[PDB]
Image (cartoon, rainbow, N blue to C red):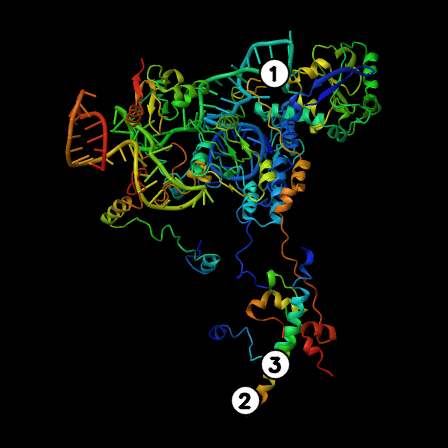
Amino acid sequence: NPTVKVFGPTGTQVAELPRPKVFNVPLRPDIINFVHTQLRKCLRTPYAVSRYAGVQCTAHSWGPGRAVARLPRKHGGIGAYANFARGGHMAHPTTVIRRWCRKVNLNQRRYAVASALAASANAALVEARGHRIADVPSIPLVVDTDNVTKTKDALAIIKAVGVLRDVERCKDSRHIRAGRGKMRNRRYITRKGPLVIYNTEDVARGFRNLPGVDLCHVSSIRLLELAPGSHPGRLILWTKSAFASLDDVYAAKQNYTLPRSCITQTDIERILQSDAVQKTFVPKRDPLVIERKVDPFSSKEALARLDPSGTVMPK
Amino acid sequence: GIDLKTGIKKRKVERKEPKSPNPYIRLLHNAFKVVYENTGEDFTKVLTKRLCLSKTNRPVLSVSRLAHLMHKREDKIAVVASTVTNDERLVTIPRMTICALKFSATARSRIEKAGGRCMSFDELLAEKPTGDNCVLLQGRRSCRAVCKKFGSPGRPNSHVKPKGEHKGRRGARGRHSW
Amino acid sequence: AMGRNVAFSNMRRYKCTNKGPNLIKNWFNQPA
Amino acid sequence: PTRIRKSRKRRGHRQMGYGRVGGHRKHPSGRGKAGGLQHKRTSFDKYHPGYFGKLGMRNYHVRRNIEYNPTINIDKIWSLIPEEQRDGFLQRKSTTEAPVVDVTRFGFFKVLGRGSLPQCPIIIKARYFSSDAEKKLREVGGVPLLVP
Amino acid sequence: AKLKNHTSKNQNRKDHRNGIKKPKKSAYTSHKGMCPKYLRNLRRSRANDPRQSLR
Amino acid sequence: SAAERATEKEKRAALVKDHAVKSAQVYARYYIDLVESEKK
Amino acid sequence: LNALRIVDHYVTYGEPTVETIRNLIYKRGFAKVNGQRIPIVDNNLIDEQLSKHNILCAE
RNA sequence: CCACGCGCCGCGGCGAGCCCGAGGGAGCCCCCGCGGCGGAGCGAGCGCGAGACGCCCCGGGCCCGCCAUGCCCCUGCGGGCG
């Protein structure tokens, strides 16, 4: 398989890393959605109303014949203990006893992590996921950094390898959020940008602050990070050690064989463009002429179409 | 005001495009639909429908039944509609060429050792669109246990089974009990 | 399948909901 | 999910698909499986024969482990051997170095017969042998030895 | 309260909606109810020679 | 392959049009026959 | 005819003269070919489906 | 509405398999991770335990148990074969 190209902090080093095979696994958007929605819902904090909410007050129904609507009422006659009443218990109370987590079987979760990484290698998928990769020279961008602890020296690698545009737009947004979110402890939405994967090459100190950059170990690649917003196609930058260890991490699973590669839409279309099946195709019957109906009697021509001998009768 | 009711008996519901969100599976039906539209070859027509069937309707045709099915003519390619999973009950399996939507990891190994080729459906489209030298087989669709407990256990003319443990003499011992 | 072919349910009826010695438990304390 | 359900579409349709002449009232005909032999006899009988009535001898506390009897069909005995040895034991044949399968340690106690063992000498070692099983095994050449 | 008793009005339309369904070929010639001796003769004879379902 | 229109289409349309003319005249002769055949 | 007598109250019936047969088949004549209602505006249509019963033309 | 039991149905992974169980791991979304459910039934039990076909589907024919029974016989109201 063509060796990927390792780019140095300013210009490519003479380093070629064989494409790890995880990249050829089919890109299934369906599985990468099912695994994600379930995985994110897995990480939630339960919300409910008080069990003693509304039921705290005391109301014995006034009852029919006193002209009061029939609803439990307090000493004066105030609405209580009803969803339609002010201060009453919501008839169906919310619950802390919910299935907050939606479990996924291990094979399926690993399937998706591979599917996202292989979509990431497709350059087109990243562009669609709203990343300005036109500058980045070769995706997967394996940028060899021994160690970076200074933010400026990290900016340096990102600017030189054409990631500058992506990082700039992550700071450029940072708008205040829309709706009740501000008061709920999520005041700022910083648009997500590139993801840097490291294997013992410390890049944590230098790349953590910059906005839109997230750092993960090769050993753990969290789906929520591999696809922001349940969409596959992240801008991915790899420290040399991490990219080299991809096919090594992918042999740690005792029985995880990679999912078999499928065929793309273009290749199946090429198979139908192929003369093999073009030869099998044979022309069918010619479509039957339908037309519209006009009175033959009114026009000599229609009478001619229906009967040639009949039309010449007037002479 | 047309009374067309007497002539017909109502529309019939049938799958047209596989509902599976698997992109790869939609692509293959679309291809066998392009091929079927151009040439009316029936193999192509059944192929289109078999991909369209439900994941329960399409059954597992294990290699041992496959070998028994093709024992007379192993040369003929067999296009199994669904997942082929090998059965180790048949110790030795003969050379066979089978085109299936999925092959189990164990199955691939058994036909590979047997010198047989497990060619994928895309390869089938490339080589044999017509289905020449190809027989389209499928497993027992009635294999499912849910198919066995379907029905009305109780009424004498069912010969099916009640769902549960029951532990009840009433009705169990003969048509004269109950 | 409301009736017709259904199994007999093996569910013991929920006990002590409104009051009771806190029968229910939740596993939210397990991450911690 | 909450958005995609029959219930949401039915909002705006009065009694919400439970009918007008008879609505969804609380516990309409019984709480539980009530009416076993009276009001709901026709449903219980048409589908679940044998709901009511004692039948078997009662063992107050069964010893579950003693009751366990995993049984391996005399076809799957051979596929217990892995393929680095499966090819060899069959190709060689030979009584002197014949394969010996201890189904006890593989996790079964009694052998049953449901097929044909491949024609190679084999010494099965198990807790008990089924008549069909031993008849086929002895004929193939194989001997059934009882395990301790 | 005095109520209706029994009347077949409308029952005919319901039944003939798509009804009059033939009983099916499997029960057209089923072996239930046949002479016990006839059954043993048919099974033993078929087994020998051409219909050797036997091995 | 697309000579289907030239092959027995203008020719088949001509065959039908011409034979319609001959059929058109004899048919009319039978219809005229009824007015007197039954009358005589 | 026996069927007609059973359902006479709805229908109406008589022997059709050649010109009624002509005008109906020429001015309101429609074809059931392929289950559609293609209008028969030209001689070719009759031939495509009724040649095998020797009905080459509308006349 | 939410929970959990159930019966179907549509998907997704895998396949005589399959299984984020509690847990353990400097790990949090990642790695490892049993009982379980099937794979064999039937019989109240002693217990005994399916090959033979077949694109599918339907029957038909057979085989397994629970029953009766006729023979033959070993190690024996035990085994075999009807």
Amino acid at the residue labelled 2: Glu
| Residue that carries the numbered disc 3 in the rendered image | F26
- Foreground mark, 1 or 3, reads 3
Secondary structure of residue under mark 1 = loop
| Residue that carries the numbered disc 1 in the rendered image | C31
Q: Is residue B70 left or right of residue A136?
A: left
Label 2, residues with CA under 10 Å away: few <14, some 14-19, many ≥20: few
Q: How far is disc 1 from disc 3 in space, using C-alphas?
A: 100 Å
| Residue that carries the numbered disc 2 in the rendered image | F38
**What chain does mark 1 sit on?**
C
Secondary structure of residue under mark 3 = helix
Label 3, residues with CA under 10 Å away: few <14, some 14-19, many ≥20: few
Amino acid at the residue labelled 3: Val
Q: Are marks 2 and 1 on the same chain?
A: no
Give the vertical position of G25 relative to D92 (above or below): below
Give the vertical position of B158 relative to D120 (above or below): below
Q: Earlier in the sequence, mark 2 or mark 3?
A: 3
Which quarter of the image is occupied by the N terminus of chain B? bottom right
- Which residue is located at x 55 percent, y 89 percent? F37
Residue A105 can be seen in this image: yes
Residue A278 - label: none
- Foreground mark, 2 or 3, reads 3
- Foreground mark, 2 or 1, reads 2
Amino acid at the residue labelled 1: Pro
- The residue lying toward the viewer, choosing from A42 and A148, is A148
**What chain does mark 3 sit on?**
F
- Which residue is located at x 70 percent, y 71 percent? A305
Secondary structure of residue under mark 2 = loop
Q: How far is disc 2 from disc 3 in space, using C-alphas?
A: 18 Å
Residue E28 position in % (x across, y down): 35, 53
Q: Is residue B160 left or right of residue A64?
A: left
